Image (spheres, coloured by chain):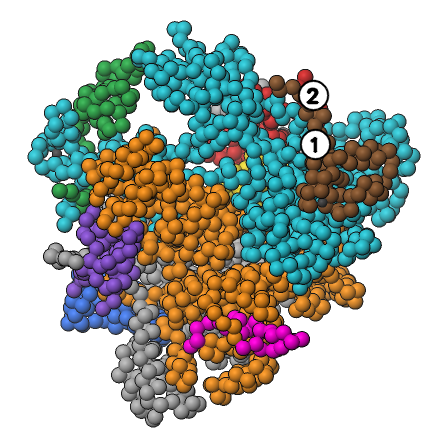
Amino acid sequence: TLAQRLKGKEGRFRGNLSGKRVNFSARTVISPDPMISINEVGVPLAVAMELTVPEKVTEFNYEKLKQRVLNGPEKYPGANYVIDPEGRRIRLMESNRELIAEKLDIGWTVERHLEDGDVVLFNRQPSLHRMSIMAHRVRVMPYRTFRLNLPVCPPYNADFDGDEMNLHVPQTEEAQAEAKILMEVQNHIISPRYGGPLIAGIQDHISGGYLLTREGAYFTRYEVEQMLMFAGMDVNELPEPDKYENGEPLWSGKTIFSLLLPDDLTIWYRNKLCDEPERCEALEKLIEEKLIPDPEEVRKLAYDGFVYIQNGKLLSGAVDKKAYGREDGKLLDIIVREYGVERARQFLDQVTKLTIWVITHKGFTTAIDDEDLPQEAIDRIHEIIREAEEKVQRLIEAYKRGELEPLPGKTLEETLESKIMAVLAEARDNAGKVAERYLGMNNHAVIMAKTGARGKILNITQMAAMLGQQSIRGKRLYRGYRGRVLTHFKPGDLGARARGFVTNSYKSGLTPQEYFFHAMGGREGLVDTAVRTAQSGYMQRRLINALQDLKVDYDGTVRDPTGIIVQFKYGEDGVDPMKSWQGKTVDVDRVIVRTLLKMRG
Amino acid sequence: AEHIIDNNLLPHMGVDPENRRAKAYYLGMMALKVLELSLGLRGEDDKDH
Amino acid sequence: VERIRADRRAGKISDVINVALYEDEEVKEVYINSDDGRVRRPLIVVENGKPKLTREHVEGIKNGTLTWSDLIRMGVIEYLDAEEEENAYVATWPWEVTEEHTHLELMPAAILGIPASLVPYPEHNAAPRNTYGAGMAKQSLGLGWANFRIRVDTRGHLMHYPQVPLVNSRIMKAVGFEDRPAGQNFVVAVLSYHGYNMEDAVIINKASIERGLARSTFFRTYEAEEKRYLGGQKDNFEVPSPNIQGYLGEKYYRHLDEDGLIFPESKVEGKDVLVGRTSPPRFQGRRETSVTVRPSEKGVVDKVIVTETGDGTKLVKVTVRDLRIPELGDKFASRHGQKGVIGLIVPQEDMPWTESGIVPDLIVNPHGIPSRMTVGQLIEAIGGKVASLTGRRVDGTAFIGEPEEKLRKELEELGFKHSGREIMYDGITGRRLEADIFIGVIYYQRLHHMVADKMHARSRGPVQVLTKQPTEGRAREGGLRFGEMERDVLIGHGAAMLLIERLLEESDKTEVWVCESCGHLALEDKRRGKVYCPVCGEDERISKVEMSYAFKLLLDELKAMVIRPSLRLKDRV
Amino acid sequence: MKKVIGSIEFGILSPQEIRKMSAAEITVPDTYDDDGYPIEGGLMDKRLGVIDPGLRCETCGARAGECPGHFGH
Amino acid sequence: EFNIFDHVLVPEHRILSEEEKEELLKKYRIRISQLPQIKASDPAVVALGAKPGDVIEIKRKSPTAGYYYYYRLVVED
Amino acid sequence: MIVPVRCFTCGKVLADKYYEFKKRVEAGEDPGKVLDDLGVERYCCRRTLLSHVELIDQVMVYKVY
Amino acid sequence: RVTSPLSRDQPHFEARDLHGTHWGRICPTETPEGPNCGLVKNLALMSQI
Amino acid sequence: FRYTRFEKARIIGARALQIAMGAPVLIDVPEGITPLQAALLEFEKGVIPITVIRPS
Amino acid sequence: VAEKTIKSMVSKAELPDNIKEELYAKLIEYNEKYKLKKDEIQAIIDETVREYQKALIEPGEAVGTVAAQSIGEPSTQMTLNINVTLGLPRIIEIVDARKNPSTPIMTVYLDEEHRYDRDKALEVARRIEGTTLENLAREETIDILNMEYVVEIDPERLEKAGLDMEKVVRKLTGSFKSAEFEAEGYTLVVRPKKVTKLSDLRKIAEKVKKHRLKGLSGVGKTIIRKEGDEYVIYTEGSNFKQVLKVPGVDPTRTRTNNIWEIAEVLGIEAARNAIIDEIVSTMREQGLEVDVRHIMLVADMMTLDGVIRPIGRHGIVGEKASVLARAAFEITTQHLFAAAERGEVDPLNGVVENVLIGQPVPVGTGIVKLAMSLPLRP
Amino acid sequence: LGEDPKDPGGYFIINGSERVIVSIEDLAPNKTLVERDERQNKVVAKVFSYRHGYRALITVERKKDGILYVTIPNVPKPVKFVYVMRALGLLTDKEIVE
Ligand SMILES: [Mg+2]
Ligand SMILES: [Zn+2]
Ligand SMILES: [Zn+2]
Ligand SMILES: [Zn+2]
């Protein structure tokens, strides 16, 4: 009845007033496209020929709109409808396309097809933040899928395992201008949530940058020219060759990477590949002592773990997630803040193509031998597992004999459980360290894990050494029969293997009991995610409805619609979190260092 | 009250008013189980078993 | 309890009866269950360290002289429910049994379901990956049924060349999946290729697609009934005349025969008429009620069925088939939970090739493999290559499958690298790749999530009667919902004009007359050409205010709820 | 020119206001007859608006899709 | 005794004068009812001896601006 | 439901020798040696020939007209 | 297919997780994603009713 | 004095709306461009006549 | 360049006070290392001023919506489930202004006389911790021959509780006057005075065992941890007012998990600070980086009226002046009928009502006013 | 007959559409399970009684006061266990005890 027609999710307010279906919208599956810019979206020709933008006939576009009308709805680029100044709508077909075209004049409206350079809204659901909808540039493609650039995926949280996305075409001039000025992709590189890069490089870009900028990486003249043409860099002559091998000139990858950076950029920091701080200490001391170190002196003691850029030249270090990755890219964040968003967009578009070319033609792959370990490592892992099992059995015997000391605030059972879990966690850490000892930097999976491109060291540990202890709700597995999880174990057995300790690894093969324990853990994780999502959405809706009306006035105050002052200054300092440097007002040290380097260089 | 007792209190014993001793004995067994669980005589029952 | 168990093993009583013994210092209970709804499993009875099942029973089973029910009858194998299994001690393997063990497991790989047994080497994969692979096993396309052409299912799929997996569990043969496969074996190389396979995307060979790989056909069945109404009125199966109301157009009936039925093997497009039908008018000429193809769908008419319903009315069923060549956005998934759409279709000349003359059918990004901890996919690739080279299919049953080290040794003995890596040459440059690329044969399944059935584009069209808002669904040419969260991001961006254009201008823009005296909605009389407020009067002070039709519906609902909303008008400037 | 809504004042409708704003009095429970035509005095009276395309409103004179509808009592 | 203002979580509270309150109202162009409110039973109010109708100047310890000034109007419970 | 004419990888014709391969496999011969004797060298063509399942005869029994 | 009468929206943490008595009766891996995770189950291949 | 993003967007929208229904361009523009492009070019040339009223 | 000149230039520059001190300290640190000149210092100051001007937020930004999105989005990747239970339930409890949070935790600091040695910390903790008779008793047995309940206790827990047997029997005898208490060995013997019914024995047996012998009410478990060469006492349960006036406890740094207790004991500003600190700590523990400005905006909106308010229908949204905004969120019929009863007027000054009607929202470009001189010619 | 030999059957055809009944994982009928509610601080035992397709939830619970209570359908408030014991035929306390 009337009460049910207003309240609820499907009520008049939420279902028809606060949110409703709209015209001039499209939706299809998305596919990757690194060749287009981050500001562009790939629109299908069928979608472009259906969605129309109403353009008024003026003096400077009469010929183009007349050609659009003459082409008709079945010939791209054409038009579907024509509106006279009287305000009536006339459908365009083959019979009357010429009559309308010769009748076109100033003041008419032509609903032409979507063309290149048009501004549209690109949205992925759910829209958790304001970066879920951004304005792109239309690029027309023959196939039936939307195309989105890879660095723009983290803002949308979109992958390509069947994701679908919505496209919206603004119809009024004011809406188009608002989308073009406020909601462009390059304008939202820095996330306002944490003041860091959001539109950044991802796995293949990071891996290609590491492959290009690592020590000992050299490329021939043909490769350098091909990657320069592929990346679209405006380079007309090659630099001086770094070294000659067998009479053939070679170029270091750092030299090619330095062409992307601006000529007046200087920054140094430690990346994720730094495992020997003693090598970075010498570089830091040399930088501090002179503040303008000689490029030859820096290259003598260059280290991959310490990246140093001097006047746009990568003198030392390798590219990783700390270079231009999401939430960690210092170089991209500095480029955005000190050179604008257009320069940052150009840098991202060039570097993504360069790294993609580097990783494509050099050859990046993973195989079954990447998780292989020598017999001595397997023996050490087995010894660690047996020692952990013996320690667990000794703890169980001590608890049975009453010699176990209770922990403060807990009884004997929880104390024994905590001790067993700590022992198993220590054993898992030791096995992971043993596995990491024998996995060098030449492994591609280790490269991916260490550079931050994709995966973690723990992911390689599970396949190589062992899985570990399976737990649900922070406790060892106990749900099952009386005194035992499974019948195959004796009742009352509190041992590690009977409670969900998987001694095997993914490569070695799980036992059926270990398979059941891993299935229990995975089910717990999936249930936890599927339960947490609804509560998070409800809390987000509550917060949105609580803080919808708050805005910053022209005097810097934040006031409610009634007029009550909530904050006399937003953030107590009047600083946008998007433009804040690591949550601070002004990065004084960075400004001082940059100004001193600019004036002394 | 008589109709509610006959047709709602443990229908699987029956709806005949004669079948009241059986309902009383079943309720006594339920109370015994409750007291055993409360005093620690017996453990909890796993609903998911 | 022992006597009851012995009687059940001797066949004196039925095997449905299950007996359990509960022993404790406080309570002592014995439970006997013989009711419905109990889920049990069979276990080999072990007596004093020796299983009751012998080699003679296996020989009798193989020879056919013994059946499973015979084995149950002698008490060698018994069904145990959850209550009886509390007192049991089951050994996982025959070589692990002791005197303490009371039962022996028959097949540890049988604890999985039918879809879960499709995944080869499930113990080498993560549990969420196995769950995803089991879930996507039911979405694959293939020769599900031999009588698919005579069926009248609303939707159907048919792979042109289905293949039995080269690496498969032995249960799949017993289940019947090998007789009705739903996928193909793909030559898969793990390599980064031009950034078009990033984020789970895949790259497929153009020549392989043109040769019929992963080719599928989509079926849709339409029905039409000559319904009979009260008073003798009934529908007619005929080509509608141009003079009747609701005429779609001359070209829409070009495939219809003189009986109102479409000819078979006729190419059709969106909104094309399949069955020409007319209906009696309501309260004039007959209306048009022809059954038409969906606007976004096309294909060729496969068959036309003429029959009758249970009431004697005529029934016509038309099946339309559409060729589905794989393209961009088509979802492809392996059996190990690795899923993704086609990112780019690459010609065979640009594709890399190995020193043995092998070109991959599919290329997957290396970044997706180690993060998800999927070693079963690599083992399956090695096993598929070994099976193709040797000619013998590789068993991939859980916990009893062929060991990985044996497969690597066989691959090394066959003349290839043990790791499965091969020397590859770049398709474009022609130079040798600096790394040995891992390439193998992986069973890949094409899922029903195709971009042809998912692409929807709406500019203008039908709207709901109640709310004057765009309809819902691609079949009814509906629009896309701009929900509350979308309004939230639009507000956060500070785009007020964009919000006005989206929520108001393009969805439910309308104009109403508002009385300036009492705030009620004024009435416009088209007969006299005058606007006035009926409740209060005020024939002069009436102004036109534009707003959403949903707001007008809300005002009407509030008035129906005995609530008076008084609209106070304000000047724009 | 054009005007916008400045404020909305809420309240409870009086019986006199309901009677004055009403276009017809509804007393017949039935909506449609056997022929499908609306019944005079019913809930689907044409004085309250029109839904069918061939119908014409007795209060507005407009067709379906543009008649806003009228309240009864 | 333990002063309520010695806690790290309790910022400095000061009662504004009549001229200071008028200047604060004039600066932000707000009425006395458009200010944030503080209850008369608040421990800071009873420690300062304030009465409803006064404006309390709060010197917050800003994590971003160092020191921030907040104003609250005393109201009855 | 019928054997592909060409290999999906390199386009080598295999449908001509499929029925002989099936006949020799059902006679107890080693499928690897049968494939070797028929000129099937690359394992992609071996993949096409080995993994194919014939199902057209099960479809012909149902008439559509 | 085996389903549960519990509501899909409620988090039934004790009911959605895999139980030790599901060995040989309920498939441990084949479960739907979302609200049906752990509440919609499938019979094991060795299961008998 | 500098324009905010909201003020710039509002000015560009108003200028594009004016160009759509008259208001000839005050600077030379290439043929075939949209009114929004003409407004953007006018803003880039610093020739816009629309001002912003701020509270005082 | 002398330090006085640098200080004078920093003071002359237009910057906030916190920026001025940091800039002066950095310039002093860099002056001795590299011998900065006057023009270099002036250029550095100008660049700092320009960067401060650039970082200022433009008017019209939807700060509330951005804050809500930037808090809700990291919650979609939070983790569910001593005994501190952080995560999404913790932030949900914080934003909902729960009167009694699940598993309250009180952080207790010590003065100079107790923060250095473990024995003083232990005795302060045992003074804070509330110990009753049921935890001290090993087993419960109802005796019928004496017609009264008999209590026995183990020596270890009695010794660790800090009070001996005589303290126990003096505690129950003073508190309970209906029955007397006698003790021999290590056993408690209770004797009635006018109790004869067996049913009256149960009501007096449970009242005896739940009586708190010592400590503060609501505190049952207490642990001690060492960090930064100082001893910090963490207790289970929250009694802020009682623990504040306890000898051996520093009240300047003592805090509790209950924000309502902070508001009742310290003040509304301290409650806002505690809310900010709790949200920041939860986000840091979850590994999610959220700018503090959103958190302070949320806390300021939560404590606008001098009391802690939730974000639901009973808090900030409930006291909104807009009828349509209130009715659109959770409760539609009740809010609309209540507005109809009172004859409320909606001024349409908010965002939700303007969205519903179809009018521009007062945010972003909606607050921009334009003017143009008509005689405009090319 | 136009049927696939590999079709397992086990479903129904209703108006030309194949309908499959999904098994329901319900509790054991006429079985009493005891559980403890830590939040409410009570011990509650529940049974589901089946008679001709009718299900009635009979709950016997004991609160902190030590008094057992019985929950009966079509009764808006729980009643004492002793009252039901008396109304079910057991008059004297000896029968209720035994
Ligand atoms: Mg996805
Ligand atoms: Zn009026
Ligand atoms: Zn009308
Ligand atoms: Zn081939």
The chain assigned the colour brown in the figure is F
The chain assigned the colour red in the figure is J
Residue A259 among those drawn in magenta: yes
- Name the residue at the bottom extreme: I2
Q: Do the residues at discs 2 and 1 belong to one chain? A: yes
Residue C412 visible somewhere in the drawing:
yes
Residue situated in front as seen by the camera: I186 or I341? I341
The chain assigned the colour blue in the figure is E
> Picture coordinates of residue A470 (x, y %)?
66, 54
- Name the residue at the right extreme: C56
Question: Circle 2 sits on which residue?
Answer: F61
The chain assigned the colour purple in the figure is H
Which residues are the magenta region?
A: A240-265
Q: Is residue A303 above or below residue F41?
A: below
> Picture coordinates of residue I209 (x, y %)?
54, 56
> Picture coordinates of residue F60 (x, y %)?
69, 23
First in sequence: mark 2 vs mark 1: 1
Real-space CA distance between mark 2 and mark 1, rounded to the nearest whole angstrom: 15 Å
Query: Quick one: SS at disc 1?
Result: loop
Q: Colour of chain G?
A: yellow
Please report the residue visible at 14 percent of the width from the left and 36 percent of the height from the top.
C515
Q: Which mark is residue F2?
A: 1
Q: Is residue A593 above or below residue A564?
A: below
Subunit under mark 2? F
Pick the quarter of the image with the C terminus of chain D: top left
Please report the residue visible at 44 percent of the width from the left and 76 percent of the height from the top.
A263
Q: Is residue J36 left or right of residue A598?
A: right
Q: Is residue E10 left or right of residue G26?
A: left
Q: Colour of chain A?
A: orange
* Number of the front mark, 2 or 1: 1
Please report contact status of discs 2 and 1: CB closer than 8 Å, yes or no: no
